[PDB]
Image: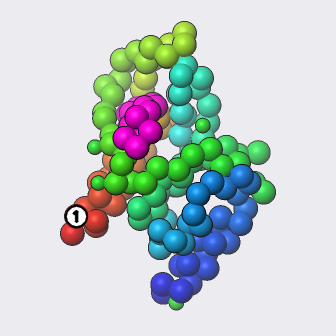
Amino acid sequence: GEFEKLEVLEEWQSHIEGWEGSNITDTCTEMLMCGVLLKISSGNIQERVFFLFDNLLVYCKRKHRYLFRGRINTEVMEVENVDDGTADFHSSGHIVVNGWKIHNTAKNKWFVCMAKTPEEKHEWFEAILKERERRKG
Ligand SMILES: [Cl-]
Ligand SMILES: [Cl-]
Ligand SMILES: [Cl-]
Ligand SMILES: [Cl-]
């Protein structure tokens, strides 16, 4: 139950190097989705591991297994679909497939994510929506 879930969240966080902000259990109670995605930010394309919790998105770089890269309160997170074959114009550019944009409205920063398959993209969309609906009731 809820106590076990907190314990598991803190175990998870303990293995992240360079954690920023409050501890995961201050805002979160369970992990809703995780997965490896390609992230394009200012034209640099890299693999990241993304974790969606209630109230929070966290992304990290693999290799302390994970290195902290960012967090977004889901209240300030917006999403925009990108249709397959659309160009991302940052640095020398990239063709986006199974992708979407994440907008951090607190920082006014945008980046592209890409999943491996349309099913995996669909799963992320559903997870993000479900998280948003929980908070809305
Ligand atoms: Cl429990
Ligand atoms: Cl990053
Ligand atoms: Cl929201
Ligand atoms: Cl949105």
Disc 1 marks a residue whose amino acid type is Lys
Q: Main secondary structure of the magenta part?
A: strand
Q: Return the x and y of residue 67 as percentages of the image width and height.
A: 70, 48
Residue 17's place in the image compared with 135, above or below, is: above
Q: Residue lying furthest left in this view?
A: 137
Q: Return the x and y of residue 121 as percentages of the image width and height.
A: 39, 42
Colour basis: rainbow
Disc tally is 1
Cβ of disc 1 within 8 Å of ligand 3?
yes
The residue drawn where x is 35% and y is 23% is 84
Q: Return the x and y of residue 28 as percentages of the image width and height.
A: 47, 69
Q: Quadrant of residue 135?
A: bottom left
Range of magenta residues: 99-112
The residue drawn where x is 62% and y is 31% is 46
Quarter of the picture holding the C terminus: bottom left
Q: Circle 1 is placed at which residue position?
A: 136
Circle 1 residues within 10 Å: few <14, some 14–19, many ≥20: few
Q: Quadrant of residue 17?
A: bottom right
Q: Residue lying furthest top in this view?
A: 92
The residue drawn where x is 37% and y is 46% is 77
The residue drawn where x is 33% and y is 28% is 82
Residue 97's place in the image compared with 105, above or below, is: above
Which structural element holds mark 1? helix
Asked if one can make out residue 122 in the rendered structure from this viewpoint, the answer is: no
Q: Return the x and y of residue 48 as percentages of the image width and height.
A: 60, 41
Asked if one can make out residue 101 in the rendered structure from this viewpoint, the answer is: yes
